[PDB]
Image (cartoon, grey):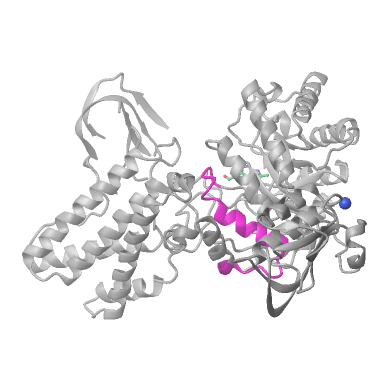
């Protein structure tokens, strides 16, 4: 499975061996980045004036003069040919030659190559990643990894703009990077250049920018410092701000100044990009002058970013026609998936889908805003690279599978199992959801429908669920121990623990449904209770961020089914045995609508609360915004949002 799939491919059902002895033609005149790749592939072999001809070069090179007609007349285009007599790797331009090589590397398997002819080129001009999320910025080693991933997948763009980098956003956007951070950035650029990726350095000055000379010069002085570190594409971001910095006329004037006094004055600047304050349709004023002012006043070479009809949305024909009419150019898409910075307790490891596959002509660029989990984001990133290169041939599920097998070949099926039950976002203020656990959803649905109704469930459905839980535990245990991609395993570990606990709880609950006798039922019930407590422990100790602390997994279908089945069987047991077992499904150590614990807060889900111990009280916040600082007073009982903060 070639990824991205090429525009045109003709395969002969013949394979040839990779020439053990070969004549290379054009090694001295082709893209050195492409030639490096080729010479690594041809490692172990040796060249001569004998052997298979291999021709590498860009249109215009002597090496590829016979193939000039077959080379696509497109930026980043290439012609690739393999037959018994010779190999051709001919780019329309230097980056095209590199992309030819990236396709060639995927064709090569077990020292053999298929007989193929390929004509290829991207449908979207700029394709890549914006590191543009709130939360812990990717680590240096993670970025190094990413840039290499992008080159392999023909993504040409890496926009650097972590909202939490103080030298990117306010107030320190004015300050040059300290020496250590500067030397790292410089290495990120060298690496990007070697992989044919434009490193795009963004700045985010809008929250405290003054529309005066001092700040304009400070901004240009910063761009200059970044240029000295080797940066050659630049962006100015005005997203998620208030106040003077939201002025569309001043924004355009600043971007035009940067364009005229800096971008068009240097010998070798490439992209100049801005993101607006009104960056999706819902946050745009139909009756306001913001987007029309930007569209009219911004110089036509400047790109304008857009997230769709909502902050989190997929791109539609009608959606993009709507933006393009106002900005008078094709939107450069900022796609908010798999970014999880507003559902920080979820991993979003599902396929990439939802974007119209017929609108390449209506976009200048397509970039994904990913999770703070860099390795985990590669599933979506690989799929986005495939989508933006050849949207006409984009295959959601095949590309997801390909990505997983690329990222974790040693445990691909186990990562598939984990990813397919870790795709949805749960309820959220952005209203964006993804499908999850689709395969078992019917069997789950019928089981619970019947079971809740004294109608007898299908045996095959009970077995499907059983099989699912078994497969979940195998996957969790194997992923935990996997050392092929240690950084990936580190990222997902807390969710993996939680996913295993979930599957164990599922199995125990199914044993309760079968329930041979009263004694056995009670043992399974007590085990479930202890498993609930364990999941609570994980949720309270892992991923304790300020915003959505903890660890949620398999939330759309599997956990609800388990929880509901549990409540149901406990109800039936209590009826049958005149008992009073507690049917509640989430462990809660405090007593009182469910209570919840978030960090050092104890809250009622929006009379009297009794904590498991005496704590120093911090304050209470009630909203029917009422508040009272508790001054460290010892508290166990509180009687009257409804949130209690304690020292913990
Ligand atoms: C032109 C779009 N700019 C945007 N800025 C914010 C980002 O930093 C967040 O990561 C994203 C998802 O929460 O939400 C918005 S979209
Ligand atoms: N060349």
On screen, residue 242 versus residue 7, left or right, reads: left
In depth, the one of 404 and 427 nearer the eye is: 404
On screen, residue 82 versus residue 431, left or right, reads: right
Quarter that holds the C terminus = top left
Quarter that holds the N terminus = bottom right
Residue 165, position as x, y percentages in the image? 60, 30
Q: Residue at x 67, y 56 (%)?
A: 41
Q: Is residue 394 magenta?
A: yes
Residue 157, position as x, y percentages in the image? 72, 47
In depth, the one of 281 and 418 nearer the eye is: 418
Residue 647, position as x, y percentages in the image? 30, 26
Q: Residue at x 59, y 65 (%)?
A: 399
Q: Residue at x 79, y 47 (%)?
A: 32
Vertical arrangement, residue 625 with respect to residue 213, above or below = below
Which residues lie in the magenta part? 371-398
Q: Residue at x 43, y 66 (%)?
A: 437
Does residue 509 show up? yes
On screen, residue 240 versus residue 510, left or right, reads: right
Residue 315, position as x, y percentages in the image? 67, 59
Does residue 563 show up? no
Vertical arrangement, residue 534 with respect to residue 580, above or below = above
Tag count: 0
């Amino acid at each position: 499975s070639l990824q991205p799939p090429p525009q045109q491919l003709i395969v002969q059902n013949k394979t040839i061996d990779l020439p053990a002895v070969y004549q290379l033609n054009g090694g001295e005149e082709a893209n050195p980045h492409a030639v490096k790749v080729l010479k690594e592939l041809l490692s172990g072999k040796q060249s001569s004036k004998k052997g298979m001809l291999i021709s590498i070069g860009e249109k215009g090179d002597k090496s590829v003069r016979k193939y000039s007609r077959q080379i696509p007349d497109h930026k980043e285009g290439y012609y690739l040919s393999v037959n018994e007599k010779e190999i051709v790797l001919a780019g329309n331009d230097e980056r095209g030659t590199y992309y030819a090589l990236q396709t060639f590397a995927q064709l090569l398997k077990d020292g053999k190559l298929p007989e193929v002819e390929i004509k290829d080129y991207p449908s979207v001009r700029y394709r890549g990643v914006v590191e543009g999320f709130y939360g812990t910025p990717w680590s240096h080693q993670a970025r190094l990894s990413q840039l290499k991933f992008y080159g392999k997948n023909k993504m040409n763009t890496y926009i650097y703009g972590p909202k939490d980098d103080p030298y990117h956003s306010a107030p320190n956007w004015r300050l040059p990077y300290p020496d250590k951070e500067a030397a790292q950035l410089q290495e990120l650029v060298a690496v990007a250049n070697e992989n044919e990726v434009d490193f795009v350095w963004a700045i985010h000055p809008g929250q405290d920018i003054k529309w005066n000379k001092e700040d304009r010069d400070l901004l240009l002085a910063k761009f200059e410092k970044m240029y000295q570190l080797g940066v050659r594409s630049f962006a100015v971001f005005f997203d998620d701000i208030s106040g003077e910095g939201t002025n569309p006329q001043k924004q355009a004037e600043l971007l035009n100044y940067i364009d005229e006094k800096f971008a068009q004055v240097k010998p070798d600047i490439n992209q100049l990009v801005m993101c607006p304050t009104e960056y999706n349709k819902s946050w745009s004023n139909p009756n306001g002058n913001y987007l029309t002012t930007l569209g009219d006043k911004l110089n036509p070479s400047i790109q304008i970013m857009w997230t769709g009809d909502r902050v989190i949305s997929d791109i539609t024909r009608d959606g993009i026609s709507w933006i393009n009419e106002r900005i008078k150019r094709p939107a450069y898409i900022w796609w908010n998936f798999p970014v999880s910075d507003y559902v920080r307790d979820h991993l979003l490891l599902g396929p990439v889908y939802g974007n119209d596959t017929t609108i390449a002509k209506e976009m200048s660029g397509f970039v994904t805003n990913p999770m703070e989990h860099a390795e985990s984001s590669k599933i979506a990133i690989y799929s986005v690279a495939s989508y933006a290169w050849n949207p006409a041939k984009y295959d959601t599920w095949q590309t997801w599978k390909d990505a997983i097998r690329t990222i974790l070949p040693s445990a691909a099926e186990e990562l598939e199992c984990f990813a397919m039950h870790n795709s949805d976002l749960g309820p959220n203020g952005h209203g964006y959801r993804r499908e999850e656990s689709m395969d078992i959803q019917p069997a789950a649905e019928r089981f619970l429908k019947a079971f809740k109704e004294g109608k007898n469930y299908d045996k095959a459905d009970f077995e499907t669920l059983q099989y699912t839980f078994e497969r979940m535990k195998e996957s969790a245990d194997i992923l935990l121990m996997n050392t092929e991609n240690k950084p990936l395993i580190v990222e997902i570990t807390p969710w993996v623990h939680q996913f295993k606990l979930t599957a164990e709880m599922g199995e125990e609950v199914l044993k309760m449904v079968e329930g041979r006798n009263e004694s056995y039922f009670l043992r399974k019930y007590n085990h479930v209770k202890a498993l609930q407590q364990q999941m609570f422990y994980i949720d309270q100790t892992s991923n304790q961020n300020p915003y959505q602390p903890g660890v949620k997994t398999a939330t759309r279908v599997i956990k609800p089914l388990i929880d509901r089945t549990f409540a149901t069987v406990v109800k039936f047991f209590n009826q049958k045995f005149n008992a009073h077992l507690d049917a509640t499904t989430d462990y809660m150590p405090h007593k009182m609508l469910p209570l919840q614990v978030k960090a050092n807060r104890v809250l009622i889900s929006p009379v009297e609360i009794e904590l498991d111990a005496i704590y120093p009280g911090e304050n209470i916040q009630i909203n029917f915004r009422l508040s009272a600082g508790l001054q460290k007073a010892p508290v166990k009982f509180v009687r009257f949002q409804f949130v209690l903060t304690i020292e913990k």
